[PDB]
Length: 307
Ligand SMILES: Nc1ncnc2c1ncn2[C@@H]1O[C@H](CSCC[C@H](N)C(=O)O)[C@@H](O)[C@H]1O
Image (spheres, rainbow, N blue to C red):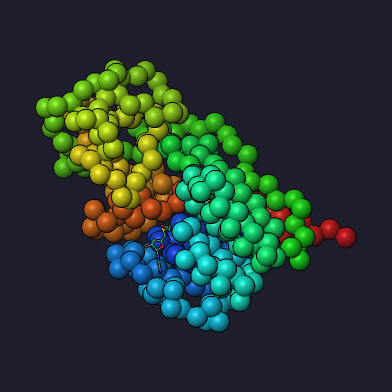
């Protein structure tokens, strides 16, 4: 996670739609924005959030009244979407910050997106979309999520600019817990196949040192000198969720706390005790660092009011 000095968001207040773990809250808040709402039905989700944010993210949005959402300047939802609009039409915030999965743009040959986008314009908001790999922002991980920044045209914001990518210098190897602490994470497997051999120095691209089993989903081991592959919250394999990583001879899955650091979360974040869950949580959450950037530049555009 990044420590942002200029709270280019101090004023504005946002709601955490589809809360999750508060990836967005973490972010904007750094930017100084204030969180007025949050909703999330997942019990263990509602659990962690509250653990680190002292509130139970209001239940299932589907039945929640948009005439109930507080007034905000940013609605963050990394998802039904029709609830957003539903709300985004009622509470018409200034900026509507969203983010989703890589394939969101392409899906159904652009339907999903043609819909959403147009559901924004027919809703009166500029639509900005672009995909960024966490790795491209001081984050060691092959993650590709979509980021949609929408502006209520009234603001006439013709200058927002997604963050400019930058080489990184922090790899998985860097975010691991003192082996002693990851011992219960090993998995002695006789059927290991070293499709490849260890690497010198480091590199940003996900080094698949070797697979296990039919070597498919959650059936691969990556080095620690590469970048943690896409954490999944629904994966199935022997090295699911996090995947397996060649950590000193023995091969082990990544630790929840490790997941975090690799998700951009700060270490202070109280992660859910249901390791199974946490994983799923992180598999579903967002890369903070990136969020922080986009956030910044979001406020940084709102703040450029000349004469
Ligand atoms: N109808 C609904 N009501 C409330 N929460 C819902 C919902 N449908 C899905 N969700 C929740 O919305 C989230 C979409 S995943 C969102 C990522 C989140 N921003 C993060 O920081 O982790 C999941 O937590 C999912 O359980």
